[PDB]
Image (cartoon, rainbow, N blue to C red; front, top):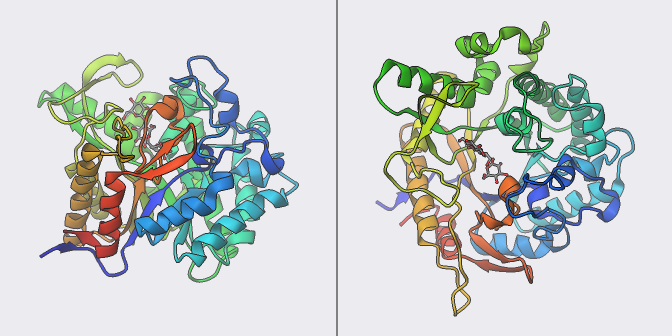
Length: 445
Ligand SMILES: OC[C@H]1O[C@@H](O[C@H]2[C@H](O)[C@@H](O)[C@H](O)O[C@@H]2CO)[C@H](O)[C@@H](O)[C@@H]1O
Ligand SMILES: OC[C@H]1O[C@@H](O)[C@H](O)[C@@H](O)[C@@H]1O
């Protein structure tokens, strides 16, 4: 009774283009909305940018050898639209495509299966100027990008993800002003949310036509376990609204052709630019649903957030350096909800991980026992999910390595591999050495 995973379980690590690649001007790449936004004062907590990051653009081969040390059989990465179509549409940048050709070729030669994210938040600035997410024109721009890159790579990439975390793209980007392009307006958020779902749905047939019969595609949702602070009818109502906002806003359209009705009413139903036939596109069948899970969020009635009329409560427990509650049972809960409610033929955890404060010891080691316990607890939740019949087919750790953590900059380290930014030295952390044995044993000791 070592608690062992299915024989073909996919163990991986995950990254994104803007977070690791650097070389922002190299080889015809144009600025993204994140190259622009990092210039805004107050936007990035340490005042940094992703200009250099981990220099993975130049160092991908060495990072792939690290992946071999970790024993992963899968790697989740994103493709930078600004490298592929630097004018947003039209003329293909061959040198951009060629990077991803080299990366994928090197992965397959090392026996690592490529899982490619098409959109992980780095729209070309010149394209945003024409089609922000709140503009319906964004959809055909994204499909065109999709068409170009899947035509080149689909002989080698079988697993495709359309867009990473619709909730982040639309709400953090356009509703809270935390993420590029840094706007703060309820209507823009809801419009962006709708066009993200529509971009997903129109890209699906294009991915399948450019591939073969083995091609698999779906979306990536962030989902957290939501909890009411108390039993009071108004804490329960507040938690329900927040869950509709965070967890059901995209899932309900994707599986049931509808937005959560009472939140839609609350917002103002006309702010969502639904045209006839849009739900038919959004519900296009997927091969899987990918989940990015990190925390439990506990909610009470209040006015900290005036849009939703909720406050966040922090229950007594363990918190990461992001101030996120560690709650591995939440992963089981989310996976079981999705299974019972939507019956996806396959689920993947495409992100799960933790930021803790890391230090390189005298001996050159990074001793991260809190990160290791975080991962151990969550792998255990995933194992129980599988035993209950949930079709979880793989698990990607966020992240391969420390990287540019968006509005937190480089101060928040999610890697199981430490990166010394002064030298670009990678050091596998204790959690990474433990992971090295989980992957090889296909399970927990
Ligand atoms: O949980 C509410 C909290 O979300 C923060 O964004 C996270 C999100 O929780 C997670 O699910 C997703 O995968 O990543 C984003 C970006 O780090 C957000 O930064 C907070 O403002 C918000 O209160
Ligand atoms: O915040 C931790 C991670 O959460 C997810 O929102 C994203 O896909 C990552 O790019 C991010 O760094």
